[PDB]
Amino acid sequence: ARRLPKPTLQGRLEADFPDSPLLPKFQELNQNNLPNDVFREAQRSYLVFLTSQFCYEEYVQRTFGVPRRQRAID
Amino acid sequence: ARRLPKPTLQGRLEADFPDSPLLPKFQELNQNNLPNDVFREAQRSYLVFLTSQFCYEEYVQRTFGVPRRQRAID
């Protein structure tokens, strides 16, 4: 019926960092008769989801081979 | 009935430091024929009160002034 209180989490991250490559898929979420704070909480959730997804990508593509046989000549 | 002896507190701080702030607040001191020593400790008390006010109002500004997000791109 209820949940834990929300964190402090002050500020909006798209207004401070609008030059990160996650912004187009981040801006896909828009409100359909949702209020301001509810959409902002869903926006914070949709931003941490894309940040987590891209950080999992940046973990995956370096741990395929952390060395490489091909960079020995390089 | 009475009180403790006063501390030493030699000299007058407002005279030796004219380039400091909070002396425009320290100008208006309501002396109505106050004696040559009673106004001295009244100057002491009001000066340390203004100094403590300035130190608290700069401490709360240094507390609310955290490493910001607009100071991260800076």
Image (cartoon, coloured by chain):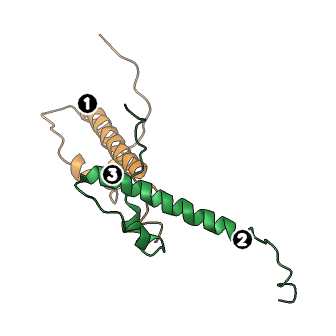
Chain colours: A green, B orange
Contact (Cβ within 8 Å) of mark 2 with mark 1: no
Q: CA distance from mark 3 to mark 2?
A: 67 Å
Q: Residues within 10 Å of mark 1 (few under 14, many from 20)?
A: few
Residue at x 29% of width, y 50% of height: A37
Q: Secondary structure at mark 2?
A: loop
Which label belongs to residue B38? 1
Residue at x 25% of width, y 53% of height: A34
Which x, y percent locates residue B51? 35, 44
Q: Secondary structure at mark 1?
A: helix
Q: Residues within 10 Å of mark 3 (few under 14, many from 20)?
A: few
Residue at x 26% of width, y 34% of height: B42
Question: In the picture shown, does residue A55 fall above or below A2?
Answer: below
Which label belongs to residue B7? none
Q: At label 1, which amino acid type do we have?
A: Val
Question: Chain letter of disc 3?
Answer: B
Q: At label 2, which amino acid type do we have?
A: Arg
Seen as rendered, the residue at the extreme left is B32
Which label belongs to residue A62? 2
Closer-to-camera residue (A58/B56): A58
Q: CA distance from mark 2 to mark 1?
A: 76 Å
Q: Earlier in the sequence, mark 1 or mark 3?
A: 3
Q: Secondary structure at mark 3?
A: helix
Position of A59 with respect to A4 (left or right) is: right
